[PDB]
Amino acid sequence: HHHHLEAPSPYSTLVVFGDSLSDAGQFPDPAGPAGSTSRFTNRVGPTYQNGSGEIFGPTAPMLLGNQLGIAPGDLAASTSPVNAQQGIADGNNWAVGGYRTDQIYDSITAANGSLIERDNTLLRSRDGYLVDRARQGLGADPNALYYITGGGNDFLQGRILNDVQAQQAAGRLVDSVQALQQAGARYIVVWLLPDLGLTPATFGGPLQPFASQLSGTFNAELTAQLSQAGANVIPLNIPLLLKEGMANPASFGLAADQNLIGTCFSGNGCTMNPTYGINGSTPDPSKLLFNDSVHPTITGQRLIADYTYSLLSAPWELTLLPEMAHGTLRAYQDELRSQWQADWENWQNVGQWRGFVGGGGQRLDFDSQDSAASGDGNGYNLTLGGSYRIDEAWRAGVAAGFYRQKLEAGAKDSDYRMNSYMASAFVQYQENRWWADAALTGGYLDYDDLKRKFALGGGERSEKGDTNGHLWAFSARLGYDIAQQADSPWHLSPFVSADYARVEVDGYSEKGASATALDYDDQKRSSKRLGAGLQGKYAFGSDTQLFAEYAHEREYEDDTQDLTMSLNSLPGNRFTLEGYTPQDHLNRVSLGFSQKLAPELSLRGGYNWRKGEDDTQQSVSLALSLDF
Image 1 (cartoon, rainbow, N blue to C red):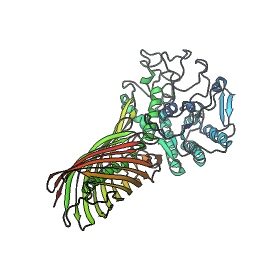
Image 2: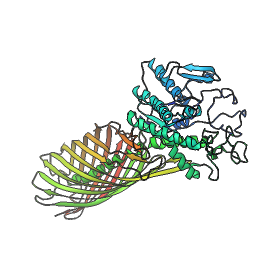
Image 3: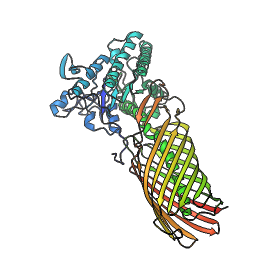
Image 4: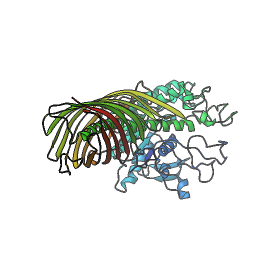
């Protein structure tokens, strides 16, 4: 039910838990305009000063939810006193600045677990997410995206001083994940803890190394526990992303000449950057990574959002790959049918081969779905074949087609290219106004160039791969000629069709092991179609003929597809996301002509138009048909 102007939007809403990394505005903003709320990142500008009247900017989950088409009201905090006083409805972001792992857990599972308190005074309180949901006979939302941060405050408060404590803290994070899973949550984004030695807070200090190694221990327990929790988690490899940013800051929109780990924008608990800091020569928070000692600036927030989005948006394109092959398979079949329609009531003599060679172009055009990217692309093909008239009423033959198809899909025009090699054996019957077709087709698929592009750092990043696949299909149809007359100049025939087609594309691993690089599972997509149609043609005296057909098909394999994958950098954490949904209806018209160039030699052309609810395919062909 997806609007075609919009990007995909798989999720009913975004529900968030965690700490200051994710808080959307639980606490009042004492130094902001009336009704302001606090987020832990820079203010929007132009002055960035406290008391300037400027609000705090957005945090990653807010930016992400927006990208994902989430209702804005959902992106607000869950328990702000400010919202209550203002009459603004509570949102789905339960993250609270200051929360340790145990508090994050309570905010999900416990009575009065969502506490907003400043200086030992309770500002506001409500029951943990699952508790409030339960008081409506509800578990988690099976269609929502869930999103969690946490662990940092455990560290700040000195509750993590050795490997054991770090592992225990990672376990408390996982407890939260499991609580949601057990409650029916089906998609959970989870942060690896950032490398805490690489924050202005500890960087270059004596705590740095112990900070870094305890961070490692935390994440190793986190990924290992999650590996065995069986929850559907999309892990964010934040530490690896940061290393990549450090090595190449300009690619993330950060200043390449600055100390991005040891200086911050605001100067709160950290060395203000002299150039881009709030009171520097040219203040610009977007040029820096850290707003204060641990909290990311607007640029960091966008990076986190874009990083999560790149992972989430991947299946919306990868799931289009089997659809490229169904596309070329169907164009291949159209080209064959065109030959049959030119041959309809007009076969070669008994015992004699009729062969053809031809080619053409095709276009694929997909509109965006809830879990599928919009995309389009051109291709070309070479097809040849031959039939042998066995008998008066029977004919058998074989055919082969080479198809080159490209597709540009997604926000950044990811570039996908495919070589399809198909062949078939077919049989035909026509006797006494009855006619019938049957075709067994096989195919090998070479996806020789797979370049996935996505927004990142105000620019774009690409990940690359190539893969293989194969397909097999059976097609049949049956009709009865309305012309009583086997020598009629025109023939007109209603028909029913049946089609099975299984396309399978092998999984593959994108090259290298960047933080954004994905490894995909095998993919398969089946089509079961029943159709009815009308075909006809008119001969203008043995030299020229025109034929056409219309068909309406029903897809019975119209379940939303899904793709299983993992980050190359985190091989033990596989997750499954939704993709292409085959629509259940398609309509086609085919036009064609045959013109004799000589006794035994016909020139033939075809045009095809296929329309589903979310796509349009087109193809044109030209062929020569000679008689042996």
